[PDB]
Length: 50
Image (cartoon, rainbow, N blue to C red):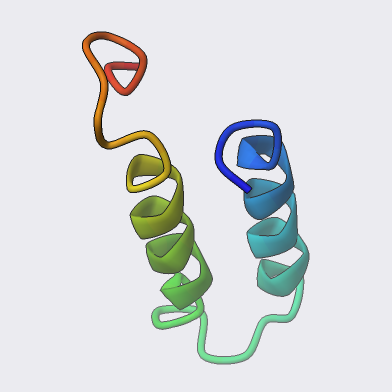
C-alpha cells in the first residue's frame, strides 16, 4: 500500500478519471493519489524526491 501500489493508486485514480463526472473536480482522485503516494514514504532521504 506504499510503493508497489504507487502504480495501482495512479491506475485506480485514472480509472475513476475515465468517469467524466465534474471534470474540474474529478481530480479529487488525483488529490487523494497525491496525498497517498507522497504520504506513503514521507519519512525518507531521497526516495520521495521523484
